[PDB]
Amino acid sequence: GPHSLRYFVTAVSRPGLGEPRYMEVGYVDDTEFVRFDSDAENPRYEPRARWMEQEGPEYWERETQKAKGNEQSFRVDLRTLLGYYNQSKGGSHTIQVISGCEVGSDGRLLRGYQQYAYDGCDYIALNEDLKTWTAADMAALITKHKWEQAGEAERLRAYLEGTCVEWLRRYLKATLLRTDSPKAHVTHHSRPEDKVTLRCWALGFYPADITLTWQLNGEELIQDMELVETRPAGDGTFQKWASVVVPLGKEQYYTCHVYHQGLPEPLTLRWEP
Amino acid sequence: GIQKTPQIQVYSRHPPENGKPNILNCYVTQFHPPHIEIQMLKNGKKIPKVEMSDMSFSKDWSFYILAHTEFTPTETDTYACRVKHDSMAEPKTVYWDRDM
Ligand SMILES: CC(C)C[C@H](N)C(=O)O
């Protein structure tokens, strides 16, 4: 299947309180593998997965020095954007970036991207051609014209097609993905008068992607069902539940279905008093 | 820019059993700006040793983080997570419900 190498970058100004806080986080297949945090006396790029200590001290010095350079460029960028938007020097602001390459099963580049946001809104994005830019407002247009006139898209296309895929191709290459199957159970809770709540739980699963449904007579109860957003247990696994309110005494007419990539086939379960 | 209001869930790592040590989570998502203050409370009083995960953000730019603390639930103790963030006029408190 496909693989991804992506970096998520945050720069937050804190006028009067010190230097901006800068973070870079690297993900292989949506799993954190390296992190740089500026909030230290001697900030270093650090491994975050069990396989990254293989890299020598040469790797860590180069990446640390790269991240420190990026940090200082985003410090400048934060100041630049105050000019572009005519904002005062007293407020905190945030720049974010997502940058990366996704390759198919065949090792060919599927998608490369470089997307910037300012204070929670899209700012500029490199287009799929890896040759042109989409600007979100008239401020970002200024950056666009600067980058068109500096061969930035050229420098990016060479990174995304070249070094990104090369590093990705070798990173965790170990190519296949962990799955932990959900364990499921149903709980029973009282409601006012002649109704009860049935809650179908899925616990201990990985990855987060999952679907829970409740069926009455073969049909999924989309309208009446309450769902929580999937949430981490804190140990690497995830949790989710779905509930329905049903008539007292009709609990055995309802079936929970759990769908997860780890399961040989979906779980079906009912309230078991 | 924008402000996004944090979404909060308070829940245990393991199914709760009275008297058995466990971990209480406060999972806070979908917020912007990234500055946030998260407290966990037992019977109304701040819990001292609350650990914070590293902060991350999603494809929609919004931030998320997990706060957690050791706890030993009992039948009558009350737990809550309180979050202060510029998107909200007052701090939001969400109580732990052992059934959710
Ligand atoms: C926010 C950054 C993309 C700004 C860019 N370096 C500029 O000076 O236009």
Image (tube, rainbow, N blue to C red):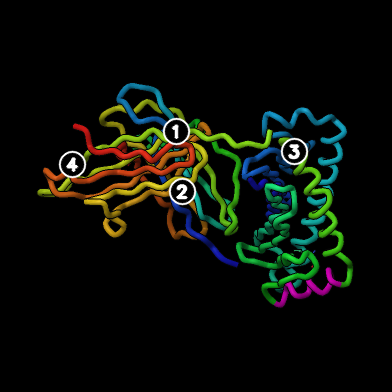
Return the residue found at the far bottom. Answer: A138
> Splitting the image into 4 quarters, where does residue A251 fall?
top left
Q: Quick one: label 3 or label 1, which is nearer the N terminus?
A: 3
Q: Amino acid at mark 4?
A: Gln
Q: Which mark is residue A171?
A: 3
Q: Residues within 10 Å of mark 3 (few under 14, many from 20)?
A: some
Distance from disc 3 to disc 2, alpha carbons, whole Å, reads: 38 Å
> In screen coordinates, is A168 left or right of B57?
right
| Chain letter for mark 1 | A
| Chain letter for mark 3 | A
> Splitting the image into 4 quarters, where does residue A27 fall?
top right
* Image x and y of residue B74, in percent: 30, 27
Q: Residues within 10 Å of mark 4 (few under 14, many from 20)?
A: few
Q: Residues within 10 Å of mark 2 (few under 14, many from 20)?
A: many
In reply to whether residue A273 is colored magenta, the answer given is: no
Local secondary structure at mark 4: helix
Q: Amino acid at mark 2?
A: Val
* Ligand 1 closer than 8 Å to label 2 CB: no
The residue pinned by badge 4 equals: A252
Local secondary structure at mark 1: strand
- The label nearer to you, 2 versus 1, is 1
* Image x and y of residue A146, in percent: 84, 71
Q: Amino acid at mark 3?
A: Tyr
Residue occupying image coordinates x 73% and y 67%: A127
**Is residue A60 visible in the rendered structure shown here?**
yes
The residue pinned by badge 2 equals: B83
Residue occupying image coordinates x 47% and y 38%: A238
* Image x and y of residue A185, in percent: 31, 35
Residue occupying image coordinates x 60% and y 41%: B54
Q: Is residue A143 above or below residue A200?
A: below
